[PDB]
Amino acid sequence: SFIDIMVFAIYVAIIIGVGLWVSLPWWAVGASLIAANISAEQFIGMSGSGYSIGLAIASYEWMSAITLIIVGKYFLPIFIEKGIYTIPEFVEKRFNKKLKTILAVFWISLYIFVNLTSVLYLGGLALETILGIPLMYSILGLALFALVYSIYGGVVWTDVIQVFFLVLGGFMTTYMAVSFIGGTDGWFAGVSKMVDAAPGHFEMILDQSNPQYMNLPGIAVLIGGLWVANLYYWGFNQYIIQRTLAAKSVSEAQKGIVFAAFLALIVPFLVVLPGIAAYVITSDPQLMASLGNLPSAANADKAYPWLTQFLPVGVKGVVFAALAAAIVSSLASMLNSTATIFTMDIYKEYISPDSGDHKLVNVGRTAAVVALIIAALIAPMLGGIGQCFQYIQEYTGLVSPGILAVFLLGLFWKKTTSKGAIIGVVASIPFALFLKFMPLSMPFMDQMLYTLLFTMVVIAFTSLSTSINDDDPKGISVTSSMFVTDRSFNIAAYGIMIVLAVLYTLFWVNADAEITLIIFGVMAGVIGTILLISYGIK
């Protein structure tokens, strides 16, 4: 690994170099939105699920497509019409600073204990499985790195470069794995061979018999808790959805949303697939003996970093470099968000009402360090959790359904009051907890749907019995010509729905048609990334 460390250092220096040396069309809005899902923690996490469950986990992304249509057509026009740039701003304009403060405490907790803890672990597993450094040291190394971008770190070209090497890295890793499965029959045999070896890894809707049903409960993927997961993700937290939109015409950006929805169908063929390939190889004793740090059920996320080691000499350095840079960039981004929420919504609001921006930034840097040391002390415990994506899923859900109910009712239910919103969001936590800690043997996704419903009922009754007036004064009232979308968006919307129908039916209907789906899907993602970067250069 002489050229390997030499190549790595060149990429790592270029990435740091481009940083120091430093309107929107529909296709840029699309690429920009989907890019968030093309991340190191996503390759590692989604492969872990691809290894443990398989393709059934493409449901998060595939259902994001239909979520994006809804978000674009309904959620967004209200944000533009009522002149909103951030979510906390929407909380303040529809409800109150008290609710905003309650939600801030939930979000900080989520970033520290769920989000950051995960990235440190998923990145820390990658360096361990590639470099050889133990986890405790490996996580700390990334933490010491993120701290540098934090205190002294204080951004577009680096993202375009980063996405490119993660995409290419993913593709190369798949081609290497699948050709190794095919042997002397080429890559084509391997795709067909992996679908023959693990048909259960290409199954979209899970049976109760399946041990993984507890994670993805069958049809609830089309009609249940996954809607809680996606609407919270795309519909509200996405500050980027409003942000990348106030970057042209609404009509144009809706074209972007629908484009991001189409690109959401391709992403699992890049991030999930390596994990399935890893499973197929791992489970073959002839293929294992051929080779001479393995993904296991308890260490599913070792799948993608395990395959990348098998990579050729120049190629290994670059792919590894991109992942490490991506993990660090993801940590810095998360650390900033946690710090801004604390400084703005907690510090400035309560501790020192008029600090001034200069003080606030220094306060934020202190907040980032604290959050990092806390997340860094927790992250080693996430070691045998199996699938980290499921951990990210389950514990965001302790708070995604409550917060999603306040948001959906604020957006649509004119009657919703702050008193209701606060009463329900608070009640949402003991309820959600009751469902996990109670011996009910209920899938978390199932719990999430119940938590949402419970909150909606609580906020609805509370607001009905407390709101003196009919519509809350802060109640959003715009409607009808607000939701109009052009025929281009609509034909694209119908297309994505018709594709999703086929995607969930293809294996059942024709198991031999799945080979075309794995190939065309993976191919569209590569061609799609290279072409979109090329027009971005123009």
Image (spheres, grey):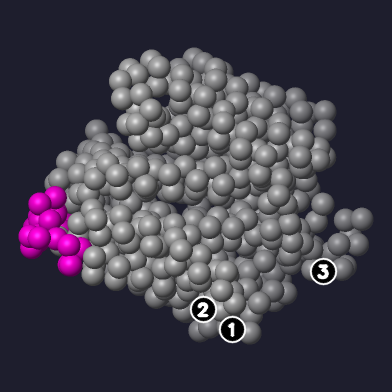
SS for callout 3:
loop
Horizontal and vertical percent position of residue 511: 58, 80
Image-quadrant location for residue 124: top right
**Vertical placement of residue 160 versus 207, above or below:** above
Residue 476 lies within the magenta run: yes
Which residue bears the numbered disc 2?
218
Of badges 3 and 2, nearer the viewer stands 2
Identify which amino acid the numbered label 3 is placed on: Asp
Q: Are marks 3 and 1 in contact (CB under 8 Å)?
A: no
Identify which amino acid the numbered label 2 is placed on: Gly
SS for callout 2:
loop
Question: Label 2: how many residues lie within 10 Å, few (<14), some (14-19) or many (20+)?
Answer: some
Q: Earlier in the sequence, mark 3 or mark 1?
A: 1
Q: Are marks 2 and 1 in contact (CB under 8 Å)?
A: yes
Range drawn in magenta? 463-486
Q: CA distance from mark 3 to mark 1?
A: 26 Å
Question: Residue at coordinates 40% horizontally, 17% vertically from top-left?
Answer: 359
Q: CA distance from mark 3 to mark 2?
A: 28 Å
**Vertical placement of residue 111 versus 45, above or below:** above
Question: Residue at coordinates 44% horizontally, 57% vertically from top-left?
Answer: 399
Which residue bears the numbered disc 3?
284
Q: Nearer the viewer, residue 241 or 518?
A: 241
Question: Which quarter shows the C terminus?
Answer: top left
Of badges 3 and 1, nearer the viewer stands 1
Residue 107 lies within the magenta run: no
Horizontal and vertical percent position of residue 31: 40, 45
Image-quadrant location for residue 98: top left
Query: As drawn, is 102 to the left or to the right of 494?
Result: right
Do we see residue 119 in this rendering?
no
Which residue bears the numbered disc 1?
208
Question: Which quarter shows the N terminus?
Answer: top right
Question: Residue at coordinates 20% horizontally, 56% vertically from top-left?
Answer: 417
